[PDB]
Image (cartoon, coloured by chain):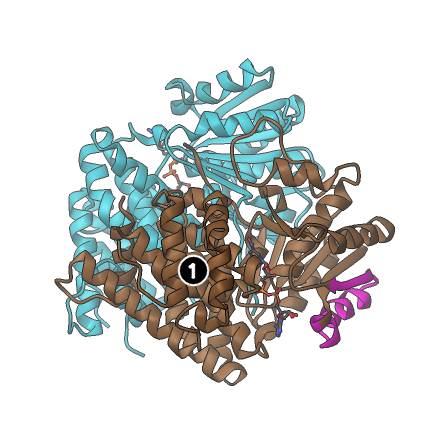
Chain colours: A brown, B cyan
Amino acid sequence: DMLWHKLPKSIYFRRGSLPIALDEVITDGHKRALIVTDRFLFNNGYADQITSVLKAAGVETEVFFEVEADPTLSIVRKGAELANSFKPDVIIALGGGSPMDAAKIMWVMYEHPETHFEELALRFMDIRKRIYKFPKMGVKAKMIAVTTTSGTGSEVTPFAVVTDDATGQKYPLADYALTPDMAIVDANLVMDMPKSLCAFGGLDAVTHAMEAYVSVLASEFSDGQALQALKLLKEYLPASYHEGSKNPVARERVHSAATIAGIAFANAFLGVCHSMAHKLGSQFHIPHGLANALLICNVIRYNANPQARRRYAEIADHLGLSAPGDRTAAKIEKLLAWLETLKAELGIPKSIREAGVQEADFLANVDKLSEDAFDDQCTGANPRYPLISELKQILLDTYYGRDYVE
Amino acid sequence: DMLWHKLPKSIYFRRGSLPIALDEVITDGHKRALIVTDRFLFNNGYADQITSVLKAAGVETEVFFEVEADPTLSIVRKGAELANSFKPDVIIALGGGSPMDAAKIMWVMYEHPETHFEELALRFMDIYKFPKMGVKAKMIAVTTTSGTGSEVTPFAVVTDDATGQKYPLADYALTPDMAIVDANLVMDMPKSLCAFGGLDAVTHAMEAYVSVLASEFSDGQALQALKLLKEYLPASYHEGSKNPVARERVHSAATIAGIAFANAFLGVCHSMAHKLGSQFHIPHGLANALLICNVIRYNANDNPQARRRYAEIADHLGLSAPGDRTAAKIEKLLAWLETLKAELGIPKSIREAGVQEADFLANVDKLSEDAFDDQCTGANPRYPLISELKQILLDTYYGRDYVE
Ligand SMILES: NC(=O)c1ccc[n+]([C@@H]2O[C@H](COP(=O)([O-])OP(=O)(O)OC[C@H]3O[C@@H](n4cnc5c(N)ncnc54)[C@H](O)[C@@H]3O)[C@@H](O)[C@H]2O)c1
Ligand SMILES: NC(=O)c1ccc[n+]([C@@H]2O[C@H](COP(=O)([O-])OP(=O)(O)OC[C@H]3O[C@@H](n4cnc5c(N)ncnc54)[C@H](O)[C@@H]3O)[C@@H](O)[C@H]2O)c1
Ligand SMILES: [Fe+3]
Ligand SMILES: [Fe+3]
């Protein structure tokens, strides 16, 4: 029953931290850097912010900018083959969850060209006690994650997910050997995020912290960070959304908050909100953060039925939502009211139906969604052990915009 | 103005985590382990808890158990020479701040026998590139007090025997590769060690929260350490091993305070405590306990503001009442600390800690000057004058509250 707190060697942050952190990459003696990113970030000059600094110091650079919305095995393999040819001694992921997750798997494949993806996907889908260990990492290259959304927190986590394009099946990988060697959290890179990305990333971060706090693997080492992320998000996410680049402090606070939520869930994991959000995302092509935003309130209601209900009340107290003499039930209602108001000002629809999913389509798939969500690796940390029938009820309630009632 | 959050690769915790973490040391392929500890911990079988597990797996072991309070250059050099002869691939510090700090410097000397101590002391006193670490050996810190948090920090201090001068080293290459926080190792701590370590931890978290280098990445951890300490230190001191939950919570709290100050640093409480400790041989945690309330009063002087931050701590700890103004929140924070100190048997003044008046008066100017110069001073939210530090020291000597 040993627990842990496992983070990157260095997390660097503050506006302008990117070039300063890169100077350490240089002085560490790195000579060949592969940047892994997407087309938007390349076309908008974000990768140049990395390569210009490295080139000035005589570091050879290559940029792979072909990561798309969800990392696919074909793209990961292509990136790995570029690594095989270019031979980087540092891989630098630049972007949101998609480039960061893709880069982690490219890194494994580069370190171990003998290893088939099937071996990785079937053996290392979760964190658990094992006899056979993850293949040794960081021999050919170190991994740096530069996050440009606020955010997935992938820059500090042992997690990656890749879609097998041949079948559409998503494969989660998890091992602390995939935790980046360095995370760079520079809010200059998120000043121009559109409103939808700001909202979805921010509510993803809220969900990460919320699930990490009530997880059966929560501890005194993660609780403070989960609560801090929630406080920062409560205090700055509205302004970040409304004002964007006009309020750089709010953008910076939220960028930090998403990483801090990462610190918590990297160690405490998540719950059934993520389980269900994964399946909604895959089935209906709803962005991850939106899917979480749609489900989180009903998951709280469900989990609140070391009771989770006491923990939710602790969050209410931390966020200043409760009044003296409030009972647990009332504190939870106040937590829910806060979340509902936050969702409203961030333009989140009130139901999956209002997010554009047709009723017949939903009903035809809801049983499969419920079964798959039960089976999801995220379910194991949820404080309430679910039945498939209960997850179905949550999904239906969320589709029709009803509050879950036990 | 880049900031950072830098911790050991792994922090492992919970009662019984030591043997479980050691199994990972074994499976990582370590073959030769040097344990660095003190005589008390060796004689009470604490080192055997490590060596028995490693030996059973065919790992060669050696123990250096000669670390004393205030590690000296002679002792560090002797430990380094043992490392040079034994050739460990892992160094495992076992103990409080003295073995942990000593082990960090032994590690550097073993990794770099070519390097003169003067080079290290004069170049790396304050957060050159540090000479590459972790080539010959990884560093594991196993803390047995609650505590210094040294198991997660980039700090070590050694005394030059020849002169009595203390040399702080600070670099993230000294951060352990692994910290092990196993409260089974602290169940039998005596009351004074419990008190002094606990109040050291309170001070670490308090100074890290109001430090000019505080950030959103450390603040939550500083507040968590303070909440854990408020909630469990009274029971830990009173009940000891009869309340293992409290002992466990406080052991975690000391490390969590470490997480905060490893990154946000400290302030003038530590600056003054270092000098009181060196001059009068007052234990570090006792020295901090004697000074912390007056440092709060000093730092809280009205013209973010430290005073707002202290009020935030009061709110976090549930010490404030609705409608309380900042001043009243701070008075409630101070009252909490005073009551905690009372339970823990902390003297009400430096005089009552056994320091003779003539001795104190003869040294107070030097204490004030040295405290100003201490590396810890730079992070303090109030930029001090030597005259003000002198006043704090005198007030604390005579048991008076500092008044602006
Ligand atoms: N299933 C899981 O466990 C899990 C968890 C996290 C991540 N993921 C995956 O990662 C992705 C989520 O990452 P994300 O939400 O951060 O976004 P993303 O990486 O999918 O990026 C989404 C879009 O935003 C753009 N973008 C990125 N940074 C920007 C910026 N600063 N300004 C403007 N546009 C920017 C990207 O170029 C892209 O077009 C999804 O594909 C999701 O499936 C999955
Ligand atoms: N800034 C820095 O670099 C830094 C960091 C840490 C500590 N330090 C210094 O090191 C010291 C910190 O020491 P500490 O408080 O951990 O104590 P310590 O290591 O000096 O040990 C104090 C005594 O407690 C005993 N002891 C330790 N663990 C015990 C246990 N579980 N049960 C019973 N007895 C036990 C030891 O054997 C010793 O006799 C201070 O002097 C401090 O200034 C400096
Ligand atoms: Fe998520
Ligand atoms: Fe201290």
Decide: is A267 above or below A196. above
For the residue with label 1, is its CB less than 8 Å from the closest atom of ligand 3? yes
| Location of mark 1 (residue) | A207
Determine if the magenta segment contains residue A47.
yes
The N terminus of chain A sits in image quarter:
top left
Q: Is A248 positioned to the left or the right of A394 in the image?
A: right
Badge 1, how many Cα within 10 Å: few under 14, some, many 20+?
Answer: many
Q: Is A145 positioned to the left or the right of B56 in the image?
A: right
Residue A233 pos. (x, y %): 41, 68
Q: Residue at x 52, y 55 (%)?
A: A278
Secondary structure of residue under mark 1: helix
Amino acid at dot 1: Thr
Residue B112 pos. (x, y %): 69, 38
Decide: is A98 above or below B277. below
* A177 or A131: nearer the viewer: A131
Q: Is residue B379 visible?
A: no
Residue A10 pos. (x, y %): 58, 54
